[PDB]
Amino acid sequence: MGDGVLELVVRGMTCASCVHKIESSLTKHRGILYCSVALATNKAHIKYDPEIIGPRDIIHTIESLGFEPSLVKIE
Ligand SMILES: [Cu+]
């Protein structure tokens, strides 16, 4: 219970192809309520249910796509 959002700076992902790579690849794992990623600040925000899946798992998941994630939550 209780939602959550976290932003990770995803170094490597930096064109529309990479955007849709992350976004589409994310929108399938349980926990993910909403993804979106933006290249302007090379950020990915994953609105994951902060219970069943953790920042670790998101890190590994994004790493599997070939871009380096590190949690920040800027805004
Ligand atoms: Cu790209």
Image (cartoon, rainbow, N blue to C red):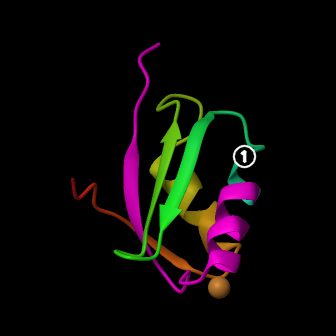
Q: Is mark 1 within 8 Å of ligand 1?
A: no
Specify whether residue 20 is painted magenta. Answer: yes
The residue type indicated by label 1 comes to Thr
Residue nearest the viewer, comparing 72 with 38? 38
Task: Determine the residue positioned at 21% across, 53% down.
Answer: 75
Identify the image quadrant of residue 58. bottom right
Specify whether residue 6 is painted magenta. Answer: yes
Task: Determine the residue positioned at 59% across, 83% down.
Answer: 15
Query: For mark 1, what is the residue?
Result: 27
Q: Which residues are magenta?
A: 1-24
> From the viewer's perspective, is residue 61 above or below residue 40?
above
Task: Determine the residue positioned at 52% across, 30% down.
Answer: 49
Image coordinates for residue 65, horizontal then vertical, percent = 70, 74
Residue nearest the viewer, comparing 4 with 18? 18
Question: Mark 1: which secondary structure?
Answer: loop
Horizontally, residue 65 falls left or right of residue 1, namely: right
> From the viewer's perspective, is residue 8 above or below residue 35?
below
Task: Determine the residue positioned at 70% across, 72% down.
Answer: 64
Image coordinates for residue 41, horizontal then vertical, percent = 34, 74
How dense is the environment of label 1, judged by Cα within 10 Å: few (below 14), some, or many (20 and up)? some
